[PDB]
Amino acid sequence: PKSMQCKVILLDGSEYTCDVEKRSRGQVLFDKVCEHLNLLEKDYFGLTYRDAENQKNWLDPAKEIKKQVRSGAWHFSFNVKFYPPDPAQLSEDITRYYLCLQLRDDIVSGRLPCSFVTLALLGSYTVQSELGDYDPDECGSDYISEFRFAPNHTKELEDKVIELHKSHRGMTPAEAEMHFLENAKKLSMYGVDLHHAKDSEGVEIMLGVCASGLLIYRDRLRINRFAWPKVLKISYKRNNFYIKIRPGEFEQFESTIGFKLPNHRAAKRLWKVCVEHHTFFRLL
Ligand SMILES: NC(=O)c1cnc(C(F)(F)F)nc1
Ligand SMILES: NC(=O)c1cnc(C(F)(F)F)nc1
Image (cartoon, rainbow, N blue to C red; front, side):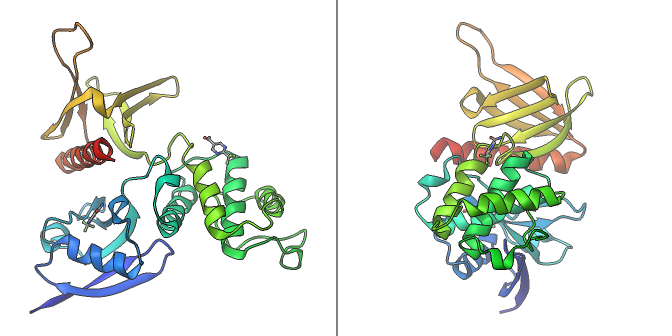
């Protein structure tokens, strides 16, 4: 029975190595990683790989690993796939902990934009969770944290993290993580998966996929939203992605909205993440 070595980048930036039989389905690897992480609320997570065009794809747990990674390395990342709209309702603190690690990367990477004060407040909860109570001995007037808090660090930001950290004395790690999440969950781009696309006139837009539905970012002054209930059908054909928007009351027919994706693979990838979000957030 021939086994393939798998390398998974965990949310703390460390590398897990394991072996699975070469015909293994994605679920096999995912279960091994989740057992390693002592994670029971696994439904919010998945594994990504980089395809032959270097795009992030979700590993499908139902299909063979080899048929997905194809010509590429058996190299994966462990990630949040479905961001809970209300992290307080997760049953385990360790679930909320991995969600925090994902969100810290979402912030540092610039995928999750965040005001100065929110960057500093989220930072202060991370520091409280990781180091415990503010200690002046570790922090002088010229202190810079090892912690990455933002896509661009300033001395003013480092100072504001410390000032807010002082306010958190006696806060336990689970408590600081819950405050981190109570704040992060409100950010306009929280759990929004962005896809570059063109509308039916060739104007460049972004499509966001999330718990509440499909978002269409045109300009700052033109953002369209389709709640999952208002979507009847999700389809792709060639480089095109279509959604069937349900008839309004007393309207005779469904409306159809058409988008152009960069290539056929980009169209299918958007279709699959949409169907998966629809199913997940229909049931949750
Ligand atoms: N959310 C899930 O339960 C889930 C399971 N398994 C996988 C895998 F194996 F493809 F990575 N991705 C997601
Ligand atoms: N833009 C927001 O929804 C938002 C979230 N969280 C905060 C925090 F941390 F300062 F309280 N400020 C703003």
